[PDB]
Image (cartoon, rainbow, N blue to C red; front, side, top):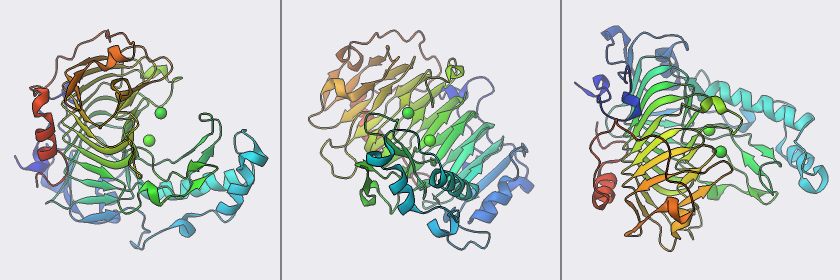
Length: 399
Ligand SMILES: [Ca+2]
Ligand SMILES: [Cl-]
């Protein structure tokens, strides 16, 4: 079968559980589309509830920050008339506002601004849909695909620069607060039976180094790359290339969302994380099989310094096998970061800078996650992960 008709293999990760991931492989020819701009993409997707099996070929670069005439949109097009960045910053400055949640005129104007952008950049992917890039240069620039539905395949696309013109200030987030943006390249928001394969994820022509600091914190225009929340389940992400980005992959959005318990069943294999700062993945609650992934970076880079790979969040059940981390100088313990409620990590065959480590034991964790993955393809020895992943992960390594 050609790319548009390929499905997830019957043993290939949590995505293959139960009914599996067939996407739009059963489509008739009247639901096979080739799209090259936002309008064509939106028309082909139809409404949230268009469950008819469909295949969507992306040809060229689809910029999502565009009006209905495909004219480019920026800050001043999206801005609410009351919003003014200068005024937002003077309102919420910790030396006059303190650490209370922003409220009043500029936060309200900011929220409405963000909604205006969201209506353009965020697109929902309905059930039984395969979206695949044609050739080696299929790109989505500015867009956030949201998948709330079952049975979706996304492959062979370079996603770039899911950029938010209206980051929110949150002074309660850590000890000096943070800026947060809304847009991922892909957000699996309660979606199920999803395969994300041979995609590339990066920050395009607007890396975080071109963002200023406000209140001493990076004015962050980006959020995740491939995130999962709100009971998302049964997902395989394979052979993708994440690079030159801060927050990569967050699975479970809140310690209060204990309905994520027994869900967030996700398999990550043969992905490349190069110059990724953090969260690769950060997990709450999920049974997440992480195997044969390659992580490379520098703790002293000036653009995207490595901080950690795996975030051991509340009641997380990461089962990690034969993953390879090349970050010179990094202490074994600091391959991971443990958050409140994070108590367990199983990891075997972890290589850090050529040396076999036990990340779980280096942090005093339990290695009992209470499950063992049965559904996986063959597991590579750790010694071959770097080559297989460098040579095979990412968009345009099929067409
Ligand atoms: Ca996100
Ligand atoms: Cl988080």
